[PDB]
Image: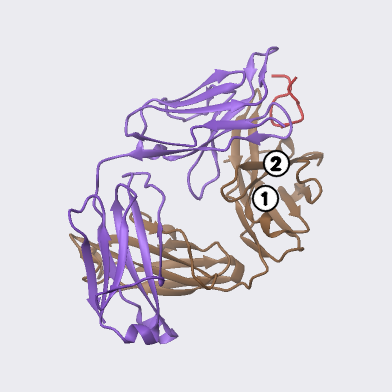
Chain colours: A red, B purple, C brown
Amino acid sequence: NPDPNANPNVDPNA
Amino acid sequence: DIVMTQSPDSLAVSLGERATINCKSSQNILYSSNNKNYLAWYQQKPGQPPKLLFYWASTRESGVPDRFSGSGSGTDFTLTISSLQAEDVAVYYCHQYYSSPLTFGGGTKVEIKRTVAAPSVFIFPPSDEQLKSGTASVVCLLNNFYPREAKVQWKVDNALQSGNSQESVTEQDSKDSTYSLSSTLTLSKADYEKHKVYACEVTHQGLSSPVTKSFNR
Amino acid sequence: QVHLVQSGAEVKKPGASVKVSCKASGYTFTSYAIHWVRQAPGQRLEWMGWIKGGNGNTRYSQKFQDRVTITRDTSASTAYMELSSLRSEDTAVYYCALLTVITPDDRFDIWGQGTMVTVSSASTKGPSVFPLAPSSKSTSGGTAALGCLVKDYFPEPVTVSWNSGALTSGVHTFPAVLQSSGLYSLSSVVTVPSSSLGTQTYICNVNHKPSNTKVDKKVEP
């Protein structure tokens, strides 16, 4: 649901 | 787009009391897969960029005092300052990084209530440099007072002035929670030289009668 | 330390373009994305876009993609934001920021200091700077008030420091006011010990980048 490309600085697999 | 709405827009609490700031998102930003809320809290003081205080709704940044805590879930979130300190006066913003575009709330301004403090009043004549340059401005300074409301009147030869002054008040001081105010009477040099007595009269809650500071040109 | 430093204040006419730089240091430039955020007067923070320091891929707000271009130069560790076809409503503070870096190994959030951009068809004008000298009318109880009047400039911002930033206790630099002329004026004042007026030197450092004005005014009794 979260867009992992909203902010690449946020671990997209946290 | 996800809209971030904050409540209240403004609040004032006494020093050491609790302050509660709410943020609502128009969409769910909790991810059931990891059970994380994709929200941050920021603190912005004047002339500064916002300072992040919380990641993931509730994870404090390193060095944030323990009186701050972030809570909530899904669409409803809360920033709580359990014992408001003078240095906490600021605008607080929530932020979602769940979807694009990144968006921020409208901000909640947090102010301090403190005891009444009367202004210290000072007056400055036009500088010789300004007079040589062809104008004359008189400055009345009201320093370190609380509450913010204060009334300044200019009198020239005991005549009440209107339409020729400008004033502004500072943000709330981050140490003593006071305000200061500067008022300028803007005159032509010709008009300044036409009169003798220049006075600024100050009304404020901490004064039992107005205080006048003046000088003779 | 992770640090972002932005270029100085700007003034442009409508229809022109502006390009703000963001110089990064204290981390591996190619590892993270730099975001650009607008803060318009009385308005909320608005995200503008991001660029990855490594491959240079970008993403823009569909409010701004029409007029914003973000680029980076890894050899200079610098990101840039160019906004074209400027409108007076683009007047705002522009920030670059390493927004919410959350990794297994690193977690931080760092902003540049902001860049004021004013878009206006009115004429730029540099300030006059006058002393507000300490006297018996500003001196009492052991403390003396003194300051600087920064009169008739356009646009914002003027910055004022005292003694090159070594004097900050007791400094009040007031918000600018508007004259009937449409020019701004502001005051900066400081309270100091009256006992040391003879040994200390007080200098207000006045900066108005739009007019290339840099003034240091000694203020004395």
Q: Is residue B186 above or below residue C49?
A: below
Q: In which quadrant of the rendered image does the N terminus of chain B lie?
A: top right
Q: In which quadrant of the rendered image does the C terminus of chain B lie?
A: bottom left
Label annotation for residue C34: 2
Q: Kindly indicate whether the residue at mark 2 contacts the one at mark 1 (C-beta within 8 angstroms).
A: yes
Q: Which residue is mark 1?
A: C22
Whole-number angstrom distance, CA of label 1 to CA of label 2? 9 Å
The three-letter code of the residue at mark 1 reads: Cys
> x and y percent of residue B197 in the render?
24, 78
Residue drawn at (31%, 62%) of the image: B152
What is the count of numbered marks? Answer: 2
Residue drawn at (33%, 55%) of the image: C170
> x and y percent of residue B78 in the render?
51, 24
Q: Chain of mark 2?
A: C
> x and y percent of residue B86 in the render?
35, 39
Instruction: Say which label, 1 or 2, has the lower sequence index.
Output: 1
